[PDB]
Image (cartoon, coloured by chain):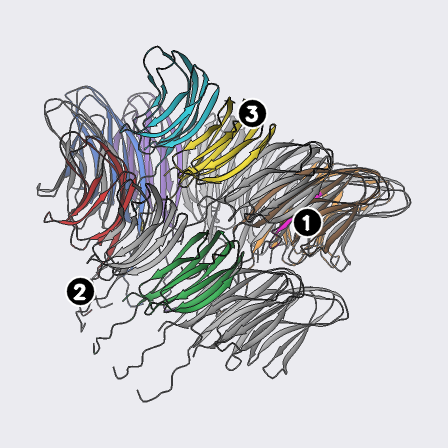
Chain colours: A blue, B purple, E orange, G brown, J yellow, L cyan, M green, P red
Amino acid sequence: ALTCCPDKNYVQDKVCSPWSGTVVATAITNVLYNNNINQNMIGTGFVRYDVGPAPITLTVLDAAGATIDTQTLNPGTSIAFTYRRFVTIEVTLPAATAGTYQGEFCITTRYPLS
Amino acid sequence: ALTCCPDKNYVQDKVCSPWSGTVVATAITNVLYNNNINQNMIGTGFVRYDVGPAPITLTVLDAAGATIDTQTLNPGTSIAFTYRRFVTIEVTLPAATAGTYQGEFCITTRYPLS
Amino acid sequence: ALTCCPDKNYVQDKVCSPWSGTVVATAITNVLYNNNINQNMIGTGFVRYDVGPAPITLTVLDAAGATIDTQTLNPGTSIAFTYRRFVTIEVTLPAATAGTYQGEFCITTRYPLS
Amino acid sequence: ALTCCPDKNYVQDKVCSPWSGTVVATAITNVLYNNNINQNMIGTGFVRYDVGPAPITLTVLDAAGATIDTQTLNPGTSIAFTYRRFVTIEVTLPAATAGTYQGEFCITTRYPLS
Amino acid sequence: ALTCCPDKNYVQDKVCSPWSGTVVATAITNVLYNNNINQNMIGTGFVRYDVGPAPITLTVLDAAGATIDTQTLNPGTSIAFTYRRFVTIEVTLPAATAGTYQGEFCITTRYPLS
Amino acid sequence: ALTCCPDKNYVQDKVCSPWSGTVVATAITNVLYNNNINQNMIGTGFVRYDVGPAPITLTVLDAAGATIDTQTLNPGTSIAFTYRRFVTIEVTLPAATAGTYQGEFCITTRYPLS
Amino acid sequence: ALTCCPDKNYVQDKVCSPWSGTVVATAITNVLYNNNINQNMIGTGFVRYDVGPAPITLTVLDAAGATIDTQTLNPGTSIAFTYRRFVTIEVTLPAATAGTYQGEFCITTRYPLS
Amino acid sequence: ALTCCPDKNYVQDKVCSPWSGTVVATAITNVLYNNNINQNMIGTGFVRYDVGPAPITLTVLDAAGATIDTQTLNPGTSIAFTYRRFVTIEVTLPAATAGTYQGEFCITTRYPLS
Amino acid sequence: ALTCCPDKNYVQDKVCSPWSGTVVATAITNVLYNNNINQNMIGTGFVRYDVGPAPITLTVLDAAGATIDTQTLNPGTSIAFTYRRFVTIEVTLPAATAGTYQGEFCITTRYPLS
Amino acid sequence: ALTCCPDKNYVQDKVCSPWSGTVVATAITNVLYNNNINQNMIGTGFVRYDVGPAPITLTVLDAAGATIDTQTLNPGTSIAFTYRRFVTIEVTLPAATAGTYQGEFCITTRYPLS
Amino acid sequence: ALTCCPDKNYVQDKVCSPWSGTVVATAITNVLYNNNINQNMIGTGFVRYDVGPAPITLTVLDAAGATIDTQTLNPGTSIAFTYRRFVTIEVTLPAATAGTYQGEFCITTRYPLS
Amino acid sequence: ALTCCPDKNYVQDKVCSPWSGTVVATAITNVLYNNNINQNMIGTGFVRYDVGPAPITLTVLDAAGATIDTQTLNPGTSIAFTYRRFVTIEVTLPAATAGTYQGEFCITTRYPLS
Amino acid sequence: ALTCCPDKNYVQDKVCSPWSGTVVATAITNVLYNNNINQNMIGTGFVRYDVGPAPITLTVLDAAGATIDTQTLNPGTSIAFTYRRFVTIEVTLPAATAGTYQGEFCITTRYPLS
Amino acid sequence: ALTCCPDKNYVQDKVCSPWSGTVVATAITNVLYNNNINQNMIGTGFVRYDVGPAPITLTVLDAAGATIDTQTLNPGTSIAFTYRRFVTIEVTLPAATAGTYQGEFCITTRYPLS
Amino acid sequence: ALTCCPDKNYVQDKVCSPWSGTVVATAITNVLYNNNINQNMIGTGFVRYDVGPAPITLTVLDAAGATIDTQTLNPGTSIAFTYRRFVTIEVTLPAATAGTYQGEFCITTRYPLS
Amino acid sequence: ALTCCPDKNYVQDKVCSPWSGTVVATAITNVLYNNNINQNMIGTGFVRYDVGPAPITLTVLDAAGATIDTQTLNPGTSIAFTYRRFVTIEVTLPAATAGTYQGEFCITTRYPL
């Protein structure tokens, strides 16, 4: 009873969703996940690129808009990741080739419920 | 037995529902979820935009009516989110194109049962 | 064995029911759910508006009769909610347009079994 | 082994039944459920009014005969409830309109098996 | 290993049966259920009155022969109940109107298997 | 590993059988069920009286031959019961009216498989 | 890992068979069931007497040849039983009336498979 | 992970077969079932004697050739059994009366699949 | 290091067992528990009398064979006790009424493991 | 996750086949079933001898060629078996009587699919 | 650090086992438990006599072969004990009545692991 | 979530086919079944020899071409088998007698679908 | 910090195994357990004799080959033991009667892990 | 309460994903996993190479781009690994042979949630 | 804080595996387990000999190649052991009888994780 | 609070995988497991040799490339092991007999987190 230092009770959630995007003349910055709890947040998951005309980019951004990690994906593959202190995950679709990009996204996130 | 500091027993619930909205001449601010327990509340989930004439906006608001996060969705896609200290989640449908917007919404929320 | 402070054993129940209401000349205040355990009660659920001549209102009231939350619904949509310390949930049907309003209601409630 | 304070083992049961009542010249006070364990009893359920000449009343009474909650129902609707420390639930049928009232009733009750 | 205080292992059974009774000149006290384990016994169920010349009475008695609860039933209805510390449940058929009374009875009982 | 106190593993069985008895000049004491495990035995079930010239008696006896419970049945009815520490259940058919008595009997019994 | 005290894994089997016996000048002791696992054995079942000139006796014996239970049956009836620590079940047919006795027998037995 | 004591996974099989035997001048010792897993084996079943000139004997033997149980059967009857630690079951047909003996045999056996 | 006075390390064990006894013509002195460590021994527990023709006696004896405490029990009851410096606990069954007495016995004993 | 001790997943198959053999001047050793998984194998089944000039022998052999069990069969009968750790089952037909032997064979085998 | 007097670390184990014995012409002295650590050993447990032709004797012996305690048991009962400084526990079966005696035995023993 | 050790999901298939072969001057090695999954494969089935001039051989081979099992068949018979870790099953037809050999083949195979 | 006298950390393991032995012309000395840590070792367990032609001997030996304890067992029984400072436990099977002896063995051993 | 040195709460996650890559004229550096928490990170898992024209390389890189470990894989095999302080895991596909490479990847990672 | 003497944290693992060996002309020295941590290692487990032409030898060796313990096994038996300071456990198969030996091996090992 | 000597929190993981290798003209050194945490690492497990033309070798190597333990396996058998301070475990397949070798591998490893 000597401290007003409460414990940190961390909890975990999971969410999966498919994503799609049609590029005609302009590039797309399709956001797949976002949060406002960037402080003390960790997320593990994958992004699956199933069908699409061309390679796409997977980028992770923090609250300041800067890029934490960027990767390149070709149709029919997957990328796994584990990130901390990020505000959003998104896929950049170039305006070069017009067409439909489709895929899936799974994430599980741990954060303090305090 | 030295403290009158009770423990915080956090609990989690889940709810899913479809949403629809018909725009004729005026914009719509279709609210999908609301609560009065904004203090110590976290919600993880997704919003799915299935069919609609035009892009829609997904916004999250706190008790003061301000905007915490705003995103843009195109027909046939999904957006995942994890938010804290919010009062409502809603979709803004512009008055530009008249028609019917349809989609789905899933959320799971953690809050103290104290 | 130093305390006469018993633990709080919280329990959860669930109930779903359809609702209907015929307006002819007078407004209706159709109550969908009520309880007498407003202290330490939380309820999560949804109200579905399926068919009806006009928009309806969904209101939540406490034991003093005041309004905690009020929302507006159009035919064919749903609204999700999570509320605490409320005495009743009801739908207000205006007397403007005469006709039949039909829908569904689901709630799951947590309360102490102490 | 320091206490003769036994634990409270709470249990839950469920029962559903249809109800009917024919009013000719006198009002009816059709009781749908009753118990003698009012201390530490909670019940969640619904009452469905299917067919009937006129609106009916749903009342909940404690062991002293007083009214805890009273609601009004129109034919073809339902009412959900969660009550504690009650002795009976009943439907009052007025003597104004003669005819047959029919409906359903579901309840699930939690009580200590101690 | 400090106590010779064994645990109470509660178990539940269920039984349903139809009942009939022909009144000619004398009242009938048709017993539907009985037990010799009145201490620590709880029973939840219903009694259904299907066909009969006149209203009947449903009574619940303890080992001393006293009445715990008494209700009145009209043909074509049902009554739900949850009782504790009772020795028998019975239906009283008046000698006023001669005829056949028929119905059903369901009960589920919890008791310690110790 | 401090105790040679083994657990009590209780098990349940079920058996149903029809019964018949022809009375000519002497009363009959038709036994429907018997056991030699009266210590820690509980049985729940029913006895159905279908056809017969006259009312019959249903009696339950313990190992000492004494009567635990006795009830009276008329043709076309049923009686439900839950008994403990009994050695047998039987139907007494009076010698007054000569004829054939027929019926059914269901029981489910719990006992330790120790 | 402190004990060489293995668990008792109890198992249950079932067997039904018809029985017949022709008495001419000598009594018959027709055995219907037998076992060599009398220690920790329990059996629940019934014996049905369908056709026969005269009443028969149903007896249950242990390994020492003594009688545990004896009952009397008349043609066209059944007897239910639940017995423990028995070696055999048999029907005694008297030599008084010559003729054929026929019936059925069902048993389900629990014993340790250890 | 403290023990190299594997669990005992018991399994059960079933087999039924008819049996026949023609006696002319010598006795027959017709074996109906045999096994080499006598340790930890239990078998429940029946032997049916349908047609035959004379009574037959049913015997059960262990690996040492000794008799565990012996019973006598007359034509048109059945015998049920439950045995443990036996090597074979057989029917002995005497050489007294020449003729054909026919019948059936059912067994279900439990043994460890270790 | 000034003393060769070792400490007394007291330990506790527990044991429960059912008891039975058949009286035919002679009284029975059924011993339920015994020990050879009467010096510095204490035992707390209960004796349960479940079924029996007549009242029984519960006696506690020391090493000299004298009686420390004697009580009388009727069928269906229990007696709790805490005794010190005793050699045995037993139940005396009178020869008056012939029959079977059955019950249970629990004890937990503390003694020095010196 | 402390052990590299995988579980044993046992599976069962079944196969039935008729068998025939013509003896002219030499004995026949007609093999009905064989396997190479003798370690941890159990088989339950039957061999049916339908038509044939003379008695035949049924033998079971292990990988070393030794005999585990041998039985004798006469035409028109069956033999049931349950064997473990065997390599083959065969029927020996003597060269004494020339002719055709015909029959059937059923087996169901359990083995680890590891 | 003034003493070479090590502490006594006492430990406890448990073992349960069934026992059987067949008497034909000679008495049996079936030993159920034995040890070579009689100095500073204490054992608490029970012996259960389930089935048997006649009363048996339970005796406890020390290393010199003398008897510490002797008791008499009848079929279907149990005896609890707590003994110190003993070498073996055994059951004496008289040669008077030939037959099989079966029962169970549980013990938990404390001894120094020094 | 501590292991990257996936489960082994075993699946089973079945295939039956007739086989024929005409020998003129050279021996035939007619292959009936083959696979490339010899690791962790088990197959149970039969080979039926219906018509043919002479005895044939049934052989089972592994990936190295060696023989696992070889058997001999005469016309009009069948052979059952259960094999593991084999690459092919074949029938060898000698060049001695010219003619047509015909028969059937059934197999059911279990393998991991991992 | 005054002593280089480390503590003795005692640990316990458990192992169970079945045993078998075939005697033809010579006696067998089947060893069930052995160790090389005889100093400061204690083992508690049982040996079960299930099936066998004749009585067997159970002996315990130390590193010098001498006998610590010897007991005699008859088929179908068990023996419990607790031993210290032993090198092996074995069963001696006499050469008198040829046959197969089968049984089980459980031990739990404590020893210093220092 | 003497230290501001918080504890390190380590947590573990798991992710599995298939990977594919089509080489035409240029080498591929297909990244399977990446993270930004290289400090205090450990990952255990495997990479499975199922189908592909030629051997591939598996490399693990840290934040500076250097190689920690490199291995070579041939089609149809797997490689297990446990690595610490790495930024990414990737497969290098040579430009020599054009074609499609496919496989799987499983990892479980431990990191501090501080 | 006076010592740089760290504690010894002992841990335990378990591993089970089947073993096989084919002897043709030369003896086999099939090693079942090996380690390089012989200092402060203890292992408890068993070796099971299931099928084989002849007796085999089980030997345990230390780092110097010397024999710590040697035992002899016959087909169908098991041997339990507890060993310390050993480098390997192996089975010696003689070259006398050619054939396949099969069996199982379980071990659990304790060692310091320091 | 007198020491900056933190505790060692040891953790354990498990991984199982099948292995295959086709030898045509050259010997193969198929690596089944590898790590970069050789200091304070212990691994217990087994290697199963199911099908193959000829005996294979199982070797365990440390960071310096030296051999800690080497064993020989014949088709259809298993070998259990418990090793410390090793960098890799591998199977050597000789170039003598051409063919496919297949088997399984299970390991559970303890290391400080």
Along the viewing direction, whichever of J40 and E21 lies nearer the viewer: J40
Q: In the rendered structure, are the residues bearing label 2 and label 1 in contact, judged by CB atoms less than 8 Å apart?
A: no
Q: Which residue lies under the disc numbered 1?
A: G88
> Distance of mark 1 from mark 3, alpha carbons?
46 Å
Chain letter behind tag 1: G
Segment tinted magenta in the rendering? G36-46
- Residue B86 seen in the figure: no
Q: Which residue lies under the disc numbered 2?
A: P5
Magenta stretch encompasses residue L69: no
Image quarter of the C terminus of chain J? top left
Chain letter behind tag 3: J
Q: Position of residue A55 (x, y in %)?
A: 17, 26
Q: Check the image and report above or below for B104 versus J3.
A: above
Tell me if mark 1 has few (under 14), some (14-19) or many (20+) residues whose alpha carbon lies within 10 angstroms of its own.
many
Q: Position of residue L80 (x, y in %)?
A: 45, 28
Q: Which residue lies under the disc numbered 3?
A: J97
Magenta stretch encompasses residue G40: yes
The answer to which quarter of the image holds residue M91 is bottom left
Along the viewing direction, whichever of M78 and E113 lies nearer the viewer: M78
Q: Nearer the viewer, mark 2 or mark 3?
A: 3
Along the viewing direction, whichever of P17 and B8 lies nearer the viewer: P17
> Distance of mark 2 from mark 3, alpha carbons?
92 Å
Q: Residue drawn 81% across and 42% down?
A: G74
Q: Is residue E71 left or right of residue L90?
A: right
Q: Is residue P62 left or right of residue J23?
A: left
Label 2 amino acid?
Answer: Cys
